[PDB]
Amino acid sequence: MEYQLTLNWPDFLERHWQKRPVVLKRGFNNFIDPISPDELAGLAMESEVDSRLVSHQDGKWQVSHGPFESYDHLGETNWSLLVQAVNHWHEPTAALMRPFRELPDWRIDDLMISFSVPGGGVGPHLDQYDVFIIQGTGRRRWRVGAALLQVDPFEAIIDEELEPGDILYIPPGFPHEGYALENAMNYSVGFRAPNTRELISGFADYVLQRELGGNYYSDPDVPPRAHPADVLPQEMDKLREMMLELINQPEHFKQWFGEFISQSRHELDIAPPEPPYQPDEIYDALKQGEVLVRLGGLRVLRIGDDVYANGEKIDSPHRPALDALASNIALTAENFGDALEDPSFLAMLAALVNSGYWFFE
Amino acid sequence: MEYQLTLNWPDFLERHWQKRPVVLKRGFNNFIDPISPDELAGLAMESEVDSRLVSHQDGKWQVSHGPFESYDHLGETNWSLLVQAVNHWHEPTAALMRPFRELPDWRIDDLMISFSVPGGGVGPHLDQYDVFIIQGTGRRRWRVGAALLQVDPFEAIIDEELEPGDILYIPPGFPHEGYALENAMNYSVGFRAPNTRELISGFADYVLQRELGGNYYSDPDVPPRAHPADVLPQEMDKLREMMLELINQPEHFKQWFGEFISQSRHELDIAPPEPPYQPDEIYDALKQGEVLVRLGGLRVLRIGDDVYANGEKIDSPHRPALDALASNIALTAENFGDALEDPSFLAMLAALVNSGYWFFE
Ligand SMILES: [Fe+3]
Ligand SMILES: [Fe+3]
């Protein structure tokens, strides 16, 4: 099954995105939850899954981290189960992502799902990132204040009670708070952006690991000074320009970024097939009609001519086939065209499959 | 005692520095070695000292690292003892440095001293750095080739036999080779420069340790694209500009560099006094005529208004007193003027002394 977003994108972009929060009434028409509260909890029981439980009694809070052996000593009110990146683990929930590809893939994060009993929620906070909160079964009251991870109470600019299929969009910076009125499922479609710090330090590691930027400062026309202990401004400029020059070299930064943002912020369900596929086995499967499916949560992005998957750079002369890898979550032989006839390309595919990044049926 | 360099600096800079090697005949007139071969070897016996022994027999080489218990099983020919940063450990040798402050302090490294028996030396190599090799007692034949850490044999553009007080200058990149003809002391005054790699990775650590560059990429006018998996050039530009912007912020980079180049490339002889000095004790000493002496090898550099010593930033409103710290290896009360009357400044001095960076007599 799949989901249709009822929403005017150019307007939402013009007037809300990264600017102003809004509640989209029945954004999803006749919304059907892709996962039961039961399924969700059973999933948080597993260790590879980043979950959390938030409770408030007597005015004080209580976070407990997953996984979870028992699901009692728990009240009937005032707690919330929050599970990170469920699109990594449950094929149906990953479909909630697809209608947001009107926003660029590289900026999309994953999907957090929360389950709360009446009164349950996390209290007033703010996020560094864009979010869409989709209301599933039940009902929740959400408050959002103007812009200024706990914060002090705030006057609300939006105060609404979401009904199934409603979507609350919140830009980064706006404080929000939400709690359940009946037993509620919320699906947060989250976004990500790097800060300058993450950029500078990650690019440095690439430079360092790959032995680049190995040219030395040279001063054949070394300037005079009055005090030998001084470092002069022009000298400082020269050092700066070495750094600018390296950042601006056409290939290196592009190539590092690709390897950086193509990585996920949460653990993937990587399960290498045994025995490994032969490039022939891949060819046969495809031509027989089998469907090659991308692993949930696995980011695949194109920067110029290169394509990157979970850190790996992928190069191939078959531009349209390679495009298919990045745009379709489910691939068939037609998507590849005559690229399947190049054994170099089959080989490349087979590697990706053996790494666990795509799998059959 | 102290040393006088007989040499025309503007010409040497115009025509040789970072351009072309040259032998300066009797650069030091009536040269007296500041250290015996005995003293040198005894010093390499100590563990805090970076030494090395290079031998060749039968065509093959043999490096052994310090320190050294016994000084036999050693031939009469074909070996060399090389000791790193002797200016850190032997007050007299540190004076060989002073006449090179016609070149900027920040570019000067330390002083390596080698002792070789006839035939001893390291064979054909090249360095990434400028050097002046001063010939002490004895005689050595040095060869230098044109420019292109072992290398293949080379035709020589300079082939000379140095006599005491001669100085061989070699820019970075030029292959050289030298061996003893009689028992020879060589004093290498070494230089240093950073590469872009060292810059980018060190600045990143500063950004990271000090919690800077924490602004996030924002795209309120996020661009349209045909394939949602693409990252567009303008997006890449925006990311780059975040990095340029941070490097160019007036204070941060200046401040990091200061903390970086003010550090030594070899271990210092840091010996914190016990008990610590009181700011009064410092004041008294100075006014009584005692001489405050900078620890050997300790770099002290000024960048704009700030002054940096072995990593520490030093700020004080007494600009000329602070200047004295960077220009004089030996300080007296006069050097400080009325800054000694500010207890804030005495306090600052006392800290530096207790760290072991300066000491009395
Ligand atoms: Fe939130
Ligand atoms: Fe050398």
Image (tube, coloured by chain):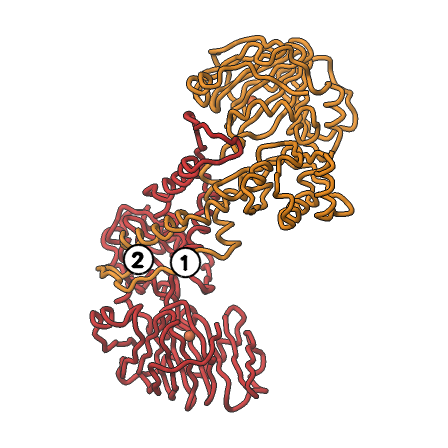
Chain colours: A red, B orange
Q: Which of the 4 image quadrants contains residue A132?
A: bottom left
Direction from residue B67 to residue A209 in the image, left or right: left
Q: Position of residue A155 (x, y in %)?
A: 39, 82
Residue at 60% over, 17% down = B4
The correct choice, above or below, for A152 with respect to B303 in the image is: below
Q: CA distance from mark 2 to mark 1?
A: 28 Å
Mark 1 residue crowding within 10 angstroms, few (<14) / some (14–19) / many (20+): some
| Front residue of this view, candidates B330 and B200 | B330
In-image side of A280 versus B361 (left or right): left
Give left or right: position of B23 versus B233.
Answer: right
| Above or below B311: residue B103 | above
What type is the residue that disc 2 sits on?
Leu
Give above or below for A172 relative to A187. Answer: above
* Residue A353 visible in the picture: no
Residue where numbered disc 1 is placed: A195
Q: Residue at x 53, y 39 (%)?
A: B261
Which image quarter has ligand 1?
Answer: bottom left
Residue at image location 45% in from the left, 75% down from the top: A125
Pointer 2 residue: A325
**For residue B89, which quarter of the picture?**
top right
Quadrant occupied by the N terminus of chain B: top right
